[PDB]
Image (cartoon, rainbow, N blue to C red; front, side):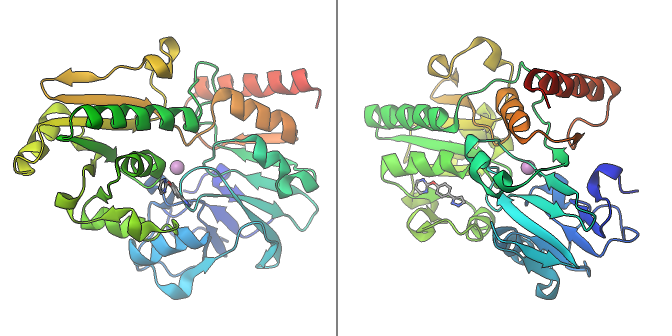
Length: 341
Ligand SMILES: c1cnc(Oc2ccc(-c3cc[nH]n3)cc2)nc1
Ligand code: NI
């Protein structure tokens, strides 16, 4: 049963709704981005029109084997008519290929669906500036004031400086970075760039990255692990046992591992500054948890919503408990009373 918050009223459209079988009345299925909770259910046997970005379409074709005849990529920042309704895709500042969707309903209502996003002041000078938005379907992942974290730029500065120091002190150190999905590519790319190395990875992860339209990508990644001193591993392997095991496989080329786990928020954020972050260490292995987020902080979310001034907000995350729903509704009312809309 497809829930109300995945349906767009007055249209034949759903958003991120592939796990409910054939949805009654749905003539077009939109996919905001290629993360598994959102694409859940898509396969080579899907036979309805899918609307998405070019990058999401590349991943659908090559990783999930969806047939080409059902993939409808749309350019960004461009008015398009889909099944009689004007739509626009906007960059969501999430992972590669992630979009927000503006729907211009036949009755004059305007709806923004953020998908997953990290709100930024630059969005205040997109096509959103042009008209009133009545309803907002909002990524509320971190909708509580305790959820603080630094800018992406500050976190990358820390990672580059940490890696460069360690490898200049010990040229036989290996750097490892954890991954379990697309997104957060800047972490491993920025480290490899400062060290003058390509990033080594599995054939499966290499395939995924080859779909993302990153400029000059062939100069930056490889499947030849032996040529590279920055390796990507599954997030599950970023622990002392898993890293010990990996070091054994490198044939005495290295004698130290420096590893990074890019999480989102962790309550380490409440006390500590990014500058003061320290690793967990056992022998010749050190692991840094770094707060690299691709979702809005509380303050970023609040600024975006107070600028947009929507008439109604529909959360799309943390919808399952009465406590979560009541907490979010209280913040939305605070924001409205403070700003006067
Ligand atoms: C050397 C090379 N590349 C980087 O970083 C990135 C470059 C491009 C993307 C990207 C994602 C979607 N479109 N472009 C992301 C990260 N850093 C150093
Ligand atoms: Ni996501």
